[PDB]
Image (cartoon, rainbow, N blue to C red; front, side, top):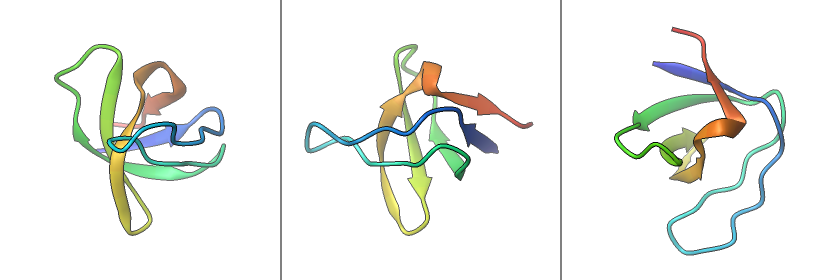
Length: 56
């Protein structure tokens, strides 16, 4: 499913990935309530679950 980046986020750890507000990301894993794995363009990593909104 797709998610919308509500805020920009700069990765701060190896598992994280950076995104820009307005970006449309592919949701890969939402099993964690605080961090969701997403694919941003061609990169994959975690971003705060609260910073994205499911479109589906």
